[PDB]
Length: 119
Length: 9
Length: 106
Image (cartoon, rainbow over all chains, first blue to last red; front, top):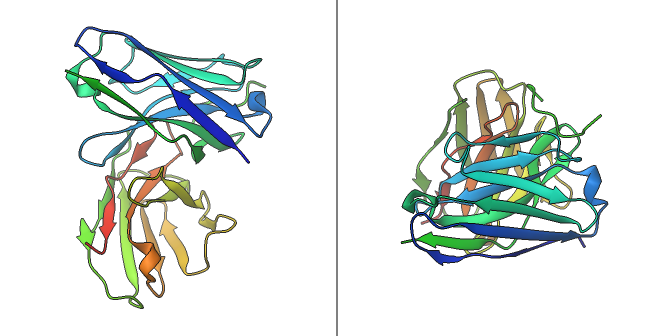
């Protein structure tokens, strides 16, 4: 019943910007922390960023700090990832993810995935 | 967990 | 930055065999080790959460144990349906790190 519907990828040139979106349903969204994870070409999974229930705390990998911004609008049930200054190294399948309970960002529910390709 | 917060208060 | 090293790299088993996938951490993770399964072309599925608890609906044949730096994932009798990649995640500290997977049966 919990759905995380993702949107917004594509192929872009290096230096571009993309806004990834994730709209959720089947749970009270403000009660949960949310994250973005990316699976790279070598099937490795890599955490990108996390945001707390109210959006007052955000964490980013050192990889994307300063170029990526995670945000949410609690009223619309959506999570965003604004990516700027896209590098080829950012090519991956990006997944919208839900933290399983209050104290942990460990993910229980994952979106279908969005390819962003930088080339 | 080891200081990251997920619930704001 | 807690490194997680998953092992083995890959394994091929016959159905009914037992498998063991280890995931070792550079630091004590207070048992916040989590296990995932990704069947080809699906999002990863949450199998076991922090404190080695099997999640609802995951079958009993999956189990895990582990000391603060050394954790183990086991499948007791491998069924056909279990081929995929298995990943472990520590959720003790940010950055959250993942092992790079183990691929089950080819």
